[PDB]
Every structure is written in C-alpha cells, then in structure tokens.
Amino acid sequence: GSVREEIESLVQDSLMEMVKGVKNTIESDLASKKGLAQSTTEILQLDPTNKAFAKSVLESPNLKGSFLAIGLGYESDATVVENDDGWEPNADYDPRKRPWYVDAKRERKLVVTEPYVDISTKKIIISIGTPVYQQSNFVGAMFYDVELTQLAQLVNSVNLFDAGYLFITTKDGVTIAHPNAENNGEKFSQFLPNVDLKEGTQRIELDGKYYLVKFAQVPSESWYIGAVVDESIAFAMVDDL
Amino acid sequence: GSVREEIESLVQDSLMEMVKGVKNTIESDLASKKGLAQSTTEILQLDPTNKAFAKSVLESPNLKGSFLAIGLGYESDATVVENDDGWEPNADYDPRKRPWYVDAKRERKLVVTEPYVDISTKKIIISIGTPVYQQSNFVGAMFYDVELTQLAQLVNSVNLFDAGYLFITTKDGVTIAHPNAENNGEKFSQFLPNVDLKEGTQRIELDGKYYLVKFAQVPSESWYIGAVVDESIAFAMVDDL
Ligand SMILES: NC(=O)C[C@H](N)C(=O)O
Ligand SMILES: NC(=O)C[C@H](N)C(=O)O
Ligand SMILES: [Ca+2]
Ligand SMILES: [Ca+2]
C-alpha cells in the first residue's frame, strides 16, 4: 500500500526522533554522571576504609546534588556509608546482595545496572556501580542512583496521529516508560501481544483493531523504543490529506 | 533577487547547523567538566592546605584524563600544585596573576575564562576557574584547562558549497577557529574588513570581490559563528541548477 508505506515512513520519523531524544538527554546525562562517579570512586581509594573520609566526600554539595543518592557498602561487615538524608538501612539490608554491588564485583569496573526497584523510594531506577579496591584487594562497591524521570517526560510529550504513542523497554522487554504508567514493570506483551522484540515493522490485530508497531534499539543502554499506531486511523488521516 | 535570496537562505541553513553543532559538542562537554571541576574543588576544600592530598587527587586517572591539565595556586604563597607532565612553573610564574585565578577570585564562584594563550602549550585554550575556601576565607584558585580542538573540527568539516566557509571568534572579535589556522589569534577584521560583529546579514566589497557574511552568537560562551561566501562564486553555482 502507498498510503500505508507513508504511515510506516512517518512512524519511522518519530521513532528516530525519539531515539535521538533519549541519547541527547538521559544518555548524555549518564555519560557526564559516569565521569563524576569514576573520579569519586578513584579519590576514595586514596583511603577506602576511612569511613569518615567517605562520608565527607559523599556529603559534598555538588556531588550530593547530582544524584538521587550515593553510597559505599563494605565487603567485610556489610555496612553502608551513604548520603540519603531521609533513608537509613533497615537491619535486613545487605549491600552485597544488591544489583549495583553484584555487577560491580563481577565486571571489576564502572557499571550501569538494568532498571530495578529502588529500596529507598520504591521507584524504578538505574544505578552506576563501581568496585572499590585497596591495592587490588576488593573491599566493597558503590552505588550512584539515577532516576528515570526524563524517560517518562519524553514518552508523555509525543502523540502519534492522536492514535498512537511511544514506549520504552529493557532488552528483555520489561516496560520502563509508557503514557499509562500501570504498565511499567510489565513485559510489553501484556498490553501488546503477538509482537516480537526486534527492529523492523510489525503489523498485528488486537481486540478488533489493527496496529502498526516499530522498534528501535538504544545500543548503549540496550533499551528498546516502541512506536505503535492504530493503522485504520492513521490511514484515515493520511488519505484525507 | 531570487538567486541571491537562495544563497542567503543556504548560508543561513549552514550557520544554524553550526550553532546547533557547537552547542551539542563543546557546550555539552563543558557542562560535564564544570560538574567535575566543581566536585574536585569541593573535595579539595576538605583539606585545602594539605598539598600532598591535592596532588594525589589531581593525579587520579579519570580526572587527569578529563582535562588538558589541572592545578592549584595559593594566595599567601603563589606556590602551585599541578598535574602537567610537561611543565613546571618557572621563577616568574605567579598563579595569582593568571586569568583563571583573577576571574575566580573576582566572581567568587566557578567561572569559564575567555580564550587565552596557555603558558605551557602556547595554544589558545579556555580554563574553568574555581575559588578555594577554608573556614570562610580565600586560600587560592584552581584551573581546569580545556582544549578548543572541537572548534577546529567543526570548521574544517564544512564548506559552503565551495564558495566560502565558517569561522569562530570571541566576543571581542579574536578568531579562535578558521579553516586556515594562521588567522587564529588575530582579529577577524584582518582577513575580513568592514564587517561588524553583530547578528544578521552583511554584504561587503574587498579587493574587487563581493562577499556575503552572516553572524550568529552562542550566548552561553558569547562566541560568534561567522559564515562567509564569495558571492560571485555562490551565484554561478546556484543559478546553474
Ligand atoms: N539507597 C538505596 O536503596 C541503594 C540502592 N538504590 C538499592 O536499592 O539497593
Ligand atoms: N599553569 C597552566 O599551564 C594553566 C594555564 N594554561 C595558564 O597559562 O596559567
Ligand atoms: Ca541516611
Ligand atoms: Ca609538572
């Protein structure tokens, strides 16, 4: 179809635009925050076990203001130095079982985690994680919490034909941004069944309607951006003009 | 008329692309470094007079790889702690008389200097400046040197349909990037007389020839981007098609 090849072309335009939106906001924020976390981690290995030192550094204003929260968890006694004014570890918190820590211990360098549920705010976030060494003795790890607010803002700022929207998922298809926020945390197949997670153009039927869907990857985070429109409506709009 | 207006239109399209490019490379990167330089400074205020701590921080890898060079010069003393492996202050060097020191002590907060000639590398650079405070008094200022290589990258990557080119100057009219590097350091009026440093379209005559020039500002640096073409060449190229 020629009107249909135009629908697809337009969906592609918005999708590419949304991919550039993500890279220019979140992705460049992370790259900047990564430099901050890496250097903070290096400065702390000047004297890693000095908790007094560690706390002073994490409470310095700009650093404290660039992240949701920052902390250091120690391998020896599972304690936590952190800068979150309103949160304290409850007796059951073990830094070493948290994903920022596991990843950092495994990869042995700066790491960005997959999205996960924050214990402090119960929001879905990501963290920068770093290993801490004392002469190549691994003595603990750090988290630098980044919130995902900007994705929610991008995903609510765009309309497709008033008959479609964009959404964002992880590499395993867990939704992390969606105009209807109930769907976050869900695999996308819960609201968009019979769709594969892959680049390309897919066409489906759902509850008596016909939808066009296209995905694109954001390789650095391994996220997917989905665009989905009602194809009957979009056809009506393009033929009418 | 029509062909002249199109020339103006094309030159404008390239000027705007160059503005967007400048904000998306060096400006973003600057924002990033400002964050880094601000946290490095606040952490050094944990122990401003401790010279050995200052040195082990500035020699930390990620930080020392983020800037051309970094240093700290003391008010009372004019002594300098720095991480340049290719420079050491001679008997004449007084940090307190350098532009980065001066601006920082003036503004009492983080600053970005105007383009100036680096005492070490002799190239034209900018520095971030930050004041250093201990228990509410000035004990010195810091520098974070940033190269301007990206500007050269930008102006050497485009060529206004082989009839002219783009160039960049400070707010005072000093060329900091030009496809022909020997103009750098000179006022732009030396190669392009009778052109005012203001936004808008100008037409001049110079040594028999006719030139079109558009300037645009990048407000947060107060730099000007200039786009110039030989208007007779541009005419031959556009009327053809
Ligand atoms: N403050 C924290 O909760 C640290 C980290 N975000 C975690 O959930 O384990
Ligand atoms: N000391 C330095 O090299 C910093 C700066 N380039 C200056 O000329 O003062
Ligand atoms: Ca706390
Ligand atoms: Ca030196």
Image: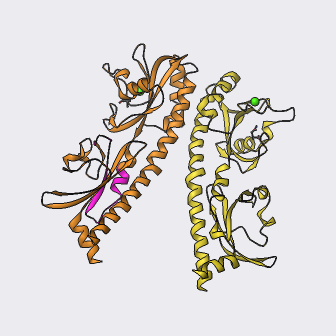
Chain colours: A orange, B yellow
In the picture shown, does residue B181 fall above or below A189? below
Residue B228 place in picture, x, y as percent: 69, 69
In the picture shown, does residue A136 fall above or below A116? above
Residue nearer the viewer, B8 or A177: B8
Residue A158 within the magenta-colored segment of the rendering: yes
Residue A130 place in picture, x, y as percent: 47, 28
Taking the image in four quarters, ligand 3 sits in the one at top left
Q: Which residues are magenta?
A: A152-173
Residue nearer the viewer, A37 or B149: B149
In the picture shown, does residue B134 fall above or below A150? above
> What residue appears at the point 49 percent right and 46 percent down from the top-left corner?
A28
Residue nearer the viewer, A187 or B46: A187
Q: Residue furthest bottom?
A: B1
Residue A196 place in picture, x, y as percent: 25, 48
Residue B133 within the magenta-colored segment of the rendering: no
Q: Residue furthest left?
A: A208
Task: Name the quadrant of the N terminus of chain A.
Answer: bottom left
